[PDB]
Image: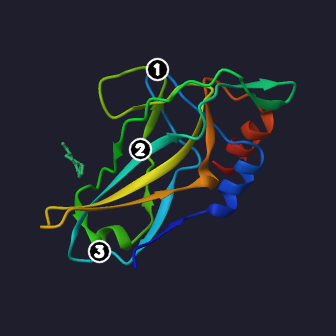
Amino acid sequence: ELRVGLEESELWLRFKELTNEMIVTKNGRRMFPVLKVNVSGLDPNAMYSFLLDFVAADNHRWKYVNGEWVPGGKPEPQAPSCVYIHPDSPNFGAHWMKAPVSFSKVKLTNKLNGGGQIMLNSLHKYEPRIHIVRVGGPQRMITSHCFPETQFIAVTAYQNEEITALKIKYN
Ligand SMILES: NC(=O)N1CCN(C(=O)c2ccco2)CC1
């Protein structure tokens, strides 16, 4: 059975208990913490490509009001995010299972841009999600996995200083 686990869940949970925030810039900003995934149960000899996207966790705009994040009352349908392909894609199952799959090079932006960067809407809440896509073989297959521990609100600057302190303490 294909097993997908979050590496460093301990640390993600400290960010999540504060409400996590991720900076977005026009040029694109790398994530801290980095999403790292433990994968087992792939066919070592099969070909797989790891895809990352961001699900809009709700349809609301969030605001930091007197020390607390609060959702607006005017939901809108959220256009789904673009997909980031892990640099090692495509690769053998053995490659992916020999160490945690680390999405250290994804950049989050607020502007439609050349390539690489993933555009998110500022002040929306996102849940990272991966797709493991068996490629090249006869039978294409996709396995998807959500990481609730890694939820964050996309921000142009940190609102909660407790997040700012944690980001620095652990980077
Ligand atoms: N350099 C490229 O044009 N890419 C082509 C698509 N790649 C994939 O591994 C993949 C599998 C499923 C969807 O994409 C990554 C490399």
Q: CA distance from mark 3 to mark 2?
A: 21 Å
Indicate how the structure is coloured in the image: rainbow
Q: Which residue is mark 2?
A: 105
Res. 66 image quadrant: top right
Q: Which label sits in the foreground, 3 or 2?
A: 3
Q: Position of residue 69 (x, y in %)?
A: 77, 31
Q: Residue at x 79, y 33 (%)?
A: 161
Q: Position of residue 65 (x, y in %)?
A: 82, 24
Q: Secondary structure at mark 3?
A: helix
Q: CA distance from mark 3 to mark 1?
A: 36 Å
Position of 52 with respect to 70 (left or right) is: left
Position of 151 with respect to 99 (left or right) is: right
Closest to the observer: 36 or 60? 60
Which mark is drawn over residue 94?
Answer: 3
Q: Secondary structure at mark 2?
A: loop
Q: Secondary structure at mark 1?
A: loop
